[PDB]
Amino acid sequence: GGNYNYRYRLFRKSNLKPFERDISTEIYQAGSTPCNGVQGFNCYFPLQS
Amino acid sequence: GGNYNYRYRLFRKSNLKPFERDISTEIYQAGSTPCNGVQGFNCYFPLQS
Image (cartoon, rainbow over all chains, first blue to last red; front, side, top):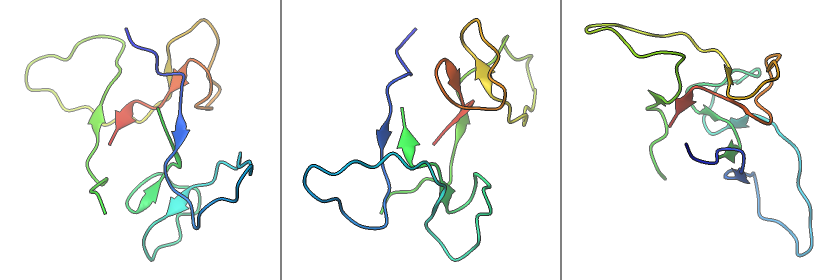
């Protein structure tokens, strides 16, 4: 059926430092509209399976 | 930059009848525990971009 329980980050405001950990799960606003925690246009979840 | 505005359904309890429109956005339960509106382990969003 496929393993869909492994994910990875796909979006961030900036890069990451060496040996740095990011665990925050916030909606990524890639446009000019307040997402307000709404998954939609220019509002993409930062994790992909 | 990649187009992400298009999504398609990936999981459903059953198949679709001919000429059917589905729009429900509900967390899917692939395991034996309630999802409780959290896309965590064995609980995946139905739409993929």
